[PDB]
Structures are given as C-alpha cells and as structure tokens.
Amino acid sequence: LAIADTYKVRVTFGQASLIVEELIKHNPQSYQILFNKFRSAISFKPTVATILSPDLLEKQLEDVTGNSLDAYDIEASHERSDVLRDLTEFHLGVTLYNAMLENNCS
Amino acid sequence: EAAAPAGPKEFTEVWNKKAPSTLIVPEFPSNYTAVKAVGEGQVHGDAFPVNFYTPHSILSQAQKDTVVLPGVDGYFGVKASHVPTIAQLKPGVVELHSGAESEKFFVSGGFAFVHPNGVTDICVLEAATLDQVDPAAVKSALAAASAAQPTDEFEQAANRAAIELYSALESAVEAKA
Amino acid sequence: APSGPFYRVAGMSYLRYSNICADLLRNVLKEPFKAKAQARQAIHFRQAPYVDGKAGASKVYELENGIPKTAN
Amino acid sequence: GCATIALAGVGAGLGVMFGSLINGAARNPNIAKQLVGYALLGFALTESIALFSLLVVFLILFA
Amino acid sequence: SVLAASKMVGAGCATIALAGVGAGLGVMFGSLINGAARNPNIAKQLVGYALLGFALTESIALFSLLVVFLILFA
Amino acid sequence: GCATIALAGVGAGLGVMFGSLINGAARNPNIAKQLVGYALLGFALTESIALFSLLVVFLILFA
Amino acid sequence: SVLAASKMVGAGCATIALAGVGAGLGVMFGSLINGAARNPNIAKQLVGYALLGFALTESIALFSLLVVFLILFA
Amino acid sequence: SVLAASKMVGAGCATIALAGVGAGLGVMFGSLINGAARNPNIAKQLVGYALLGFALTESIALFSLLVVFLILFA
Amino acid sequence: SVLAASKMVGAGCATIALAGVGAGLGVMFGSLINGAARNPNIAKQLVGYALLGFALTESIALFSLLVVFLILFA
Amino acid sequence: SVLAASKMVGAGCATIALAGVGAGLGVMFGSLINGAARNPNIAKQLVGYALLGFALTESIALFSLLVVFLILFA
Amino acid sequence: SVLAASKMVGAGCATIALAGVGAGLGVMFGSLINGAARNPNIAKQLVGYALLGFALTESIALFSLLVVFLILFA
Amino acid sequence: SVLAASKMVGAGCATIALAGVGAGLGVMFGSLINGAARNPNIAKQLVGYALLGFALTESIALFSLLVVFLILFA
Amino acid sequence: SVLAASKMVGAGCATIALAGVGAGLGVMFGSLINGAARNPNIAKQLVGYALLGFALTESIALFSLLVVFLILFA
C-alpha cells in the first residue's frame, strides 16, 4: 500500500480513519507504525507504536494467571470480543493520526 | 498462555542482536506517559484525575470528583475508587463536576475507561460544549433523518446513528439549568 | 453475517461509525464554531495498491464535508 | 376465593412487562411509541389468561 | 353431596396454575420491549419469536383449563 | 381470605414496575417524566387486577 | 362459634398479600440503591420516585388490610 | 364416598405445578427474544435451542399431568 | 373449642407475609453490595437508602405482626 | 376409608414440587439461548453444559415423584 | 383436644415464612460474590454490608420464630 | 385411622421443599451457561464450582427427604 | 387421634421453609459461577465468600430443622 498527498491541506482524524480502515481490509494480528516523534526542534527519535488485533493476539498477551483485562467491567451493548474489535480500530486510528501529525511536525 | 514475553524493555535487548549497532533503540509510546493503570495511588480521597480527551483537543486533564458519563446502558457517574470499567458511550452529555461548578460537553460517542488506580480516561471524537450547539437546525436534520428509510443496511445504520444522536441532543437542550 | 452492534453487522467499522457521529455533530454547531470544525472535517489524501512491487491502480479522496455516509 | 389466586401471577406479569417498557423507553425514546404498541399487544394476550381465570370463577359460582 | 362440594374446591385450586401463565408471559412480553429497544430493525422478526413462544406457553393455559374441565364435568 | 391472596403479585409486580422507574430515570434523567407517564399508565392498567380481585372479594361476601 | 372461627382462619389467609407487597418494596428499594449507584447526582429525584413508588405500592397493602378487617369486624 | 371427594381436591391442587412450567417457559421463550435481538444471524439456531428446552420442560409439565390422572382414574 | 383453635391456625397462615418481606430484604441488601461495589464513595449514602428502604419494608412487616396479634388477642 | 382418601389428597400436594423444577428448567434453558447468543463458537459445549445441568435437576423432579408413589402405593 | 392440635398445625405453617428469608440470604450472599468479583479492593468493606444485611434480614426471621413460640407456649 | 391418614397429607406437604431446590438449581446451572460463555478458557473451574454448589443445595433436598421418612416411618 | 395426627400434617407443613432456602442456594451458587467467570484471579476468595454465605443461609435451614423436630417431639 502507498498513501500519499496527506499533508496537502491538513491531517484530520477522519482522514486517518480512512487510512486505518484500509488496514482492516487486510486482517493482521499486529500493526507496526514507524514514525518520528517530534520531541523538540532538534531531536526526533523514531518510534514503533504497536497495535494488536482484538482477540487475534491482544487478549492473549494480557492473559496473566487469569487476565489483566478481567479487572474491567465491560459496559458495551455486545460482548468483550466485539467491543475490543471496536476499540483496537480506534486504537489504530488514534496512533495513525498521531504518527502522521508527529511526523509532519518532525 | 503468555509465551511471548513482549514489552518495551524486552524489545531493547532483542533489537540489539538483529539491527546494526550504529542505531539507538526506537522509542515507544510507554516512554511518554507516567500515568499507568495498575500503578497504585492516584486518588487521594474525593477528587480523581479525569483525562477527557479528543483527537484535536485535550479538554480537561485536571481532577474532578464526579463525572457523569453517557453509557450505552444509560447515564452513570464515576466516583473516586470506582470499579475498573471500559464503557462504550452513546451520543450524550459528559458532565464534569469538581464541586459547585459543572461543565457540560455533548460528545459524539467514544469509550471511557476507568482504570484500577482510579483515573478516568474519556476518549471521544467530537466533544462540543452545549454553548455552541444550535437548537434550530438539529430538528431540521432530525426530521430529515426520520424520513430517508432505505433498504440499504449501510445507510440504515448511518440513519440510525443520525436519529439517536439528534434525539439525545434535543433532549439535552430542552432541560438545561 | 457479522455478530455485534448495529454498525458492525451492517459491514461498517467503528471508525467510520464514530466519525459519522462526529460528522453529524459538527453540522449542528453554532456558526462562530461550525466553520472552524469544518477544518478538522475535510479528508484530502490518496492511496494506491502495490500488488507486484512498482505498479498499481489509484484512488483519490478530495472531500471537504466529512467521511462518506454511503458504503465504501 | 381460592380460584382468583390466578390473578396474583397476572399482577406480577404486568408489572414486569410495564417495568420493561420504562427501561425500554430509557434506552431509545424514539421507538417508545412502538413499545406501547408492543406492550398493549402483550397486555391483551396476558389478560386473556386473567379472564380465563375469572370465567371459571363465574362458572364455579354461576354454573 | 360430598363430591359436589369437592369439585368446586378442587377446580378452584386447579385454576391457580393460570397464575404462572400470567407471570411467565409478563417476562416474555417484557422481553420484546427490551428486545425492540436494543434494535428496532429486527422488531418484527422477534414478534415471529414471541407468538411462537406465546402459543406454546398457552399450551399450559389449555392444559390447566383441561384439568378444570376434567374435575367438574370427570 | 383466600380471595385477596391475588393482591400479592399485584404489589409484587408493582415493585418491579416502580423498580424500573428508578433505574429508568437514573439511566436518562432527561426523559425522567415521560417514564412516569408510562409508569402511571402502566400502574393504573396493572391495578385493573387489583380491582378485579377486589370485586371478587365482595361478590363472594355480599353476593 | 363457627363463623367466629372462620373469621380467624380467614383473616390469616387474608394477610398473605403482604408477602407480595413486602417483596415488591424490597425490589423497588433495591433498585433505589442501584439507581443511586449509577449516577448519585440524580439520587434526590429517585427518592421522589421511590417514595411516590412506595406510597402507591402500599395502595394494595391497604387494599389488602381493609379486607383483613372487613371480614373480621364486618 | 370420602375417596371419591378426595380425588377432586387431590387432583385440583395437583395441577398447580403448571404454574412453574408456565412461568418457566415464559422466561425461556422471552430470552430468545433477547437472544434474537443480540445476533439475528443465529436467530434460527436459537429456536433449535428453544424447542430442545421446550420439550424438556413439557416433560416436567406431563410429569404433573400424569399424576392428575393417576389420582383421578387410578 | 373451634373459636380457640382457629385463632392459632389462623395465626400461622398470617405470618407467611414475612416470607416476602424477608425475600424483598435480600435483594435490597444484595443490591447494596452491588451498589457499593460500583462506587464506594457513595457507600455511606446508599446505606442511608438501604435503611430508609428497610424502614418502609418493615412498615408492612409490622403491619403483618399486628394482624397476627389482632387475630390472637383481639 | 379416610386413609384411602388421604393418600390421594397428599399426592396432589406432593406434586406441587414440579412447579419449581419446571421453573428452574426454563431459567436454565433460557440461559442456553442467551449463552449461545453471546458466542456461537461454544454452542456445543453449552448444550453439553445444559444437559449435564438438565439431568441433575430433573433428579429432583423424579425425587418428587418417588415421594408421590411411596405415599400412594405404600 | 383441638386447641393444642391447631398449635401443631398452625406452628407448622407459621415457619414457612423462612422460605423467603432463606431466599433473601441466597440473593444477598449471592450478590456479595459478584460484588467482590468486580472490585476486590472493597471486598472487606462489602462483607461489613453483607453481615449488616444478614443480621438484619434475620430480623424478619427473628419476627418469624417469635410467633412460632408465641403459638406453642402462649 | 386419622393418625395413619394424616401422614400422607403431611408427606405431600413436606416434599414441596423439592420445588425450590429445583428452581434454584435451574438458576445455578443457567448461570454456568452464561458463565462459560464469557471465558471458556476457565470453563472447567466453573463446573468444579457448580457441582460443589450442587452438592450443597441437594443437601437441602435430602434434609427435606430426611423429614419425609421421619414422618412416614418414624 | 387428631392431636397426634396434627404433629405430622403440621411438620409436613413446616418444612416448606426448605423450599426457598434451596432456591436461595441456587441463586448464591449461581453468582459464584458468574463471579468466578468474570475474574479467575479472585476465584478462591469468592468460595471463601460463598461458604461465608452458605453457613449463614443454612442457619435458616437449621432454624427450620429444629422447628420440624419441635412439633414432632416437643
């Protein structure tokens, strides 16, 4: 995939959602986001921000002698398996929106 | 069950064996936040940290003593040592109270997490305050949204989201204090 | 065919759903704050698949009012 | 007198049904006018049994 | 008549089974109100699940009214 | 005496119907009085059993 | 004193209806706690609905406590 | 004729077990209306799970309807 | 001596109004646990709703306990 | 012949216990439909949990019927 | 001697008020399990609310076995 | 033989305690279907928690069956 | 023999308190399954809270089991 012409007008979350929604067309177990963290005008350390697919691998990595996700009371309409389906696309679209905004200022 | 011992710390010494030695390790989003979930503390009594966020704004990051959140089951309120909660929110009014003063933001939907240390992390997309909403054109589009009923289930879902958004928005512009 | 909320069963993702509810909130803001919310509503980018390595088709987004309500 | 105790379950039935409409209208108030169309459809099909009970009271007493 | 007094006292107790038909159908007809409040799009296919459940629970309402019929008039 | 045991489930159902008026108002206080128009319509309609079971307790005693 | 004896065994069965309004108020005051634990800043409006709910659920309790005394003293 | 009277009072209060089966199938067929509102893409399989549960609760309903005839006619 | 005996068998059927009052008080105090498990900074205010609920739950328990006395000693 | 009368009137009081097992089996099989509407991936284990749960509560339905025949024919 | 014979029957049917009070402690101590499964940080504060409840729904049980000895020995 | 007759009408009333243990056990086995639908990774500890919850609530059933054979043959 | 008869119809009508007690133990041991199915880290503390509830709701069973021997043998 090749996304371009993204900083032409500005970077918005609805644009970064459509860029993210093209990455749920493929269904990986993880997402790797390589960008430059704008710390100051001098230093730009690169960043790897990782987003795991909801129960493909994400709840498997929270599972410790039980789970670290079972502390939370789910207050959704449907199950925990499809609120995390809603929540990691939202975790993908947030980190994507931050990546191409931290990079554009870097 | 956890055969992949991942993390930012473990990624460092593994990356020093496959990458060239000239590069420092990439940073991680854990290195830019000190507020964790299981880090015990972070309440001190009555007022708890409320990180009400937005993609384009940080609307509040100071502490409040009760937050009225519009969950999909209904409106609930968060006290200091609330139970850990991942709450999906409807379009509704997030009410921030720290005492006698009360700000009302109407949000579009988006989750709100209560972590085990007592920090509330409201995470919505569009969070307009009720001072800058109009009570006129909301029913001008809601009566329009109560008309276009197609058999297309994609637009049927977006018209359903069109209905319940303006229905809760009108219900929270009628009964203002 | 999907099993979940009303947006998810209808094929729609949560990202397009929650942006639709963000798009429709901005259409009913007050005009001293409605036009500045139109800045964060516009979608201007383009995409291209790469199936072989160098060749691919194209797709251009030039929207200024928000995420598309109809099916993608 | 021991026959009309069938109305105790009908009194417990309409309270659960009309309580489930207060909760139903508290979720989405737009469908709330179709809920009373479903409540009274459920109320009449519940009072069928409530008048099934008193009719045999009117057959124990008057037949 | 010890039997004619006994049939009214019997069939009076026999019709209180219609309390459970009145009580269970409140939970079933309250279920479609919260079944319609969660998704109005499928609010008529669930009526196709209510009347299939309503008539199969009035099997009990006619089985109890069969016993009221079989005390007094066997 | 046995005729007014039918008043058990009427009061036991009404505590669930008014148990939903609290939970319904605590789930959206903006619609909190349209629910009472749904409650008192449902209360008066579920009292019909409380009037049916009390017309029986006089039709036995005085008729 | 058979009618005086049937007034004693009748009035005990007449007050079984307080088990229903006793379990009704415990449900309604049980959701008063659960309603005031969802959002406690509305908890002054719920007791305005709970005490209206209490006094109107007793309606049946006082409907049933008149006919524990209508059969005894009349 | 004390036994001929006792079969009417005995089988009268025998069939009040159809209260719980009528109230049991009201909460079973009601949960399908909540079940077919969560995912209507399984809403045919849930009837395959209701009727397996409906036949097994009817089995309890004909256990009691066996005794209402085994008192009356045996 | 049926007038003396029917006061005492009428008393035992009178105090089964305490079945539901004890059953209502369990879901009221059970929801105080779940009420104080969501947000325990209201666990002082919700106990003030539990005892306000218990005092009006007993309102019909003490009404049941005077009726069992009015058929025993009045 | 009061012993031949009281075995019939006791057996109808003995089979009231088929209300509650008729009531629990609707709750359990109503939870089968709700439990299989949450995750259809486990829709065979829950029926294997249902009929391990059905046959272990019916045991009390047949224990009730073991008291019916032991007072009727013994 | 029907005076003490109704003391045998009346004190029998008096103590079935303990059905619902045993059901109240089943709901109340049932609600302590999931209330302590949600936040175990408060799980020692809730047993102080459960044993406040267990001792004070018993008050209905203490009002229930009061009248069972008030029949047999008064 | 009113001494021999009253045991059969007593043993029928004594086994209505098998109503509630059937109705609770349907709730307990229905709560496992909803329990195993949340996390099937720990679905076997729940069945280990069900049969412990079963064998302690059948303990009410056999304590009530202890009373029936203590009336009928003791 | 009516007084010696009344001990066994009395104690037969005394152990219906063990109906709702076991209906309580189904609700309490059902929420233990749901309490364990939420978080398994605390699944051994909740059984410590279940038998904290079990030995206190059985007290109502032994508050009934002593009375069912108080009618028969005192």
Image: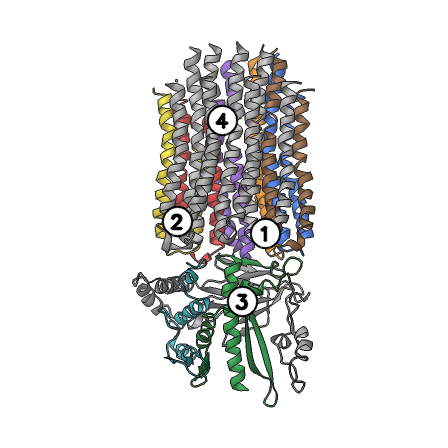
Chain colours: A green, C cyan, D yellow, F red, G purple, I orange, K blue, M brown
Is the C-beta separation of discs 1 and 2 under 8 Å?
A: no
Q: Is residue F46 above or below residue D27?
A: above
Q: Which mark is residue A53?
A: 3
Q: Is residue K24 above or below residue A24?
A: above
Circle 1 sits on which residue?
I35
In the rendered view, does K66 fall on the left or right side of C63? right
Chain ID at mark 1: I
Q: CA distance from mark 4 to mark 3?
A: 69 Å
Amino acid type of the residue that numbered disc 4 sits on in the rendered structure: Phe
Mark 2 or 3, closer to the camera: 3
Mark 3 or 1, closer to the camera: 3
Amino acid type of the residue that numbered disc 2 sits on in the rendered structure: Gly
Is the C-beta separation of discs 1 and 4 under 8 Å?
A: no
Circle 4 sits on which residue?
G69
State the SS at label 1. Answer: helix
Residue at the image point whose x is 64% and y is 51% from the top: K36
State the SS at label 4. Answer: loop
Q: CA distance from mark 1 to mark 4?
A: 39 Å
Mark 2 Cα within 10 Å, few/some/many (few <14, many 20+)?
few
Whether residue B86 can be seen here: yes
